[PDB]
Length: 50
Image (cartoon, rainbow, N blue to C red; front, side):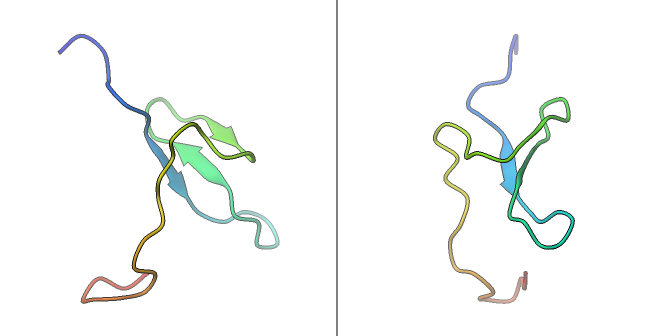
């Protein structure tokens, strides 16, 4: 509509193997965990792997 509601981040990995969170909104990045990130459930489960 006007602006994007709720936060949009995804947990991945960086150099070496550090679990970081990226931003799809525009394309931001941060080490720390974003506000109400909530992104980690059923790790490697079901049909969709990884």
